[PDB]
Length: 44
Length: 44
Image (cartoon, rainbow over all chains, first blue to last red; front, side, top):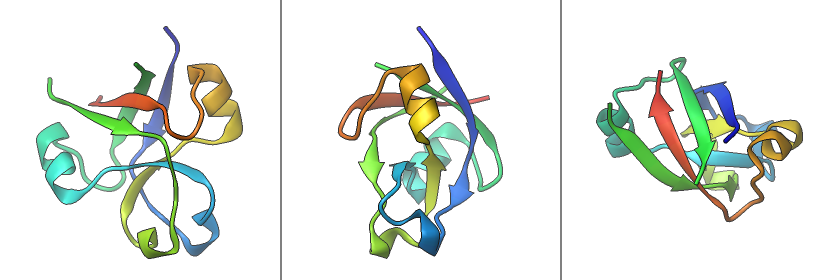
């Protein structure tokens, strides 16, 4: 299966309407990431 | 390693300033996802 290498970012005003995966504070604590960290996005 | 189960969403105006992973059209084609699809986010 293919996957996307990406970085946690702070959504910008120009990002409205664009496709994103939201990662809230609790989810970030679980994964152990802060803004700027590299993550992998995989299709389920 | 822990991972987050999430869904591709359309960023809202209230999402500005919040942490997201941006997935553009090309990236979505690679992963094979559309808005509404379940994905897994893993820390690298």
